[PDB]
Image 1 (cartoon, one colour):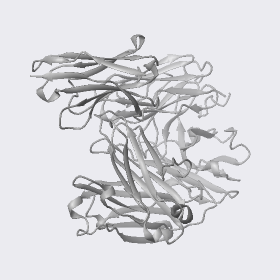
Image 2 (cartoon, helix red, strand yellow; image 1 turned 30 degrees about the vertical axis):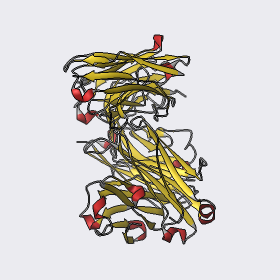
Image 3 (cartoon, each protein chain N blue to C red; image 1 turned 90 degrees about the horizontal axis):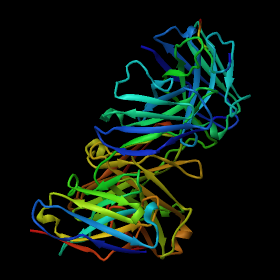
Image 4 (tube, rainbow over the protein chains, first blue to last red; image 1 turned 135 degrees about the horizontal axis):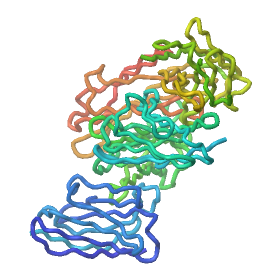
Length: 119
Length: 212
Length: 10
Length: 224
């Protein structure tokens, strides 16, 4: 399984972006996909998880109400809609597949990251 | 014997949400279906009978629909009193209940704090060694705890216990207890619990050396 | 009637 | 309003008998059929038996047929469940419930449930718990927060209560639901998160009480 993130870039405060995470090979329809972010000096930080369609989405305190995850199982892709961006949201964003279908957070495969800069 | 099936078993939901849960029967039960609500430590309470008739005293935001084999219960706008477990019951031929659907308090993600505790010298003096791994204040509920003794995965010698959602912050805490004999415990050195949770980018491991 | 019929006084 | 109060539950050895009773008030008991329904973690909600308003007809679940007898005393407003040849899988909370009023051609179920009475079928003998400290250290410290606790092991039957420092410490206490071990004895832990800077100087004591055996243990938990 290979993951590839895209959609990052430079955005103004209050602007919007949408990140995408395409997966190749394994059909991810049965697997949760999560977004994490890392800024320099800090550790990787959970952002959001899109479980299987019907099982809901859960978010981190810092992005609740501003970010939304969605799935395109036909294209093996998940998305992170980012609205009302703030300088604090600047980071590289990674997606990871939870290889445990029962959602225990077994993140075996990671993407290479996409860069988000808010200023 | 009429089989009943409820989906989903757990729904994470919020105040003000429109909630629909489903109940299905293995054969036609016409409209002879009742819905019961149960709060923890409390007796069940009748909400709906005849598939769609509200019991007196039940607020109007509850409704039911269905006939034959497919049935639903809908809460039009969820309120905090509705966080409970809901059971359907066919009463067409004897009485059988569904497995129940728990409406769970949705909140933001919180990764667990992980702590490990070695066996006390008092218990070891008695011939048994209990090792305890604690996952504190996490959400959502799904987590995995693996025990490793000298880097070997344990299977069949541990038990887990989970609290209800905390009244103050709606989180869970989980304990995993590894139980060995004194002789088994002293035939090894490194004791570790490894924890994964959807809020953790990497697994968290806490460990100690026997004697240390 | 059957087990599910009226078990109350009439 | 309608009220149902069950009684008679307790610990009974496999193969012995037990008589549950259900006191009814707030309605005309003799006018209504009644159910016994039980709930266990292993089988969920499980109908047990029904009796007509006049005692004339009774029906039973297959799992209890030939062993249980439902009966009623309409002069005393009391419903009974005589349980014979009890097995381990009969362990449950037992509820009486009143049948609702309806139309002549309806099918019927229950509208009011009692509070429930617990039945434990086990060959385990009454025994107080051993209390062992869950000692804090660097392995139970993350930042300025540390976890400590008490392991309350090998008691029968339920329940036990745990307090900390005789009640003065309640913020951050988690007492877990008991788990049944392969020995037939229960075990649980109680934990609490404390300022890591207070370890070794502040005294922490869990107060464990187990009324069925008159056990009281005050365990001091010291760091390693």
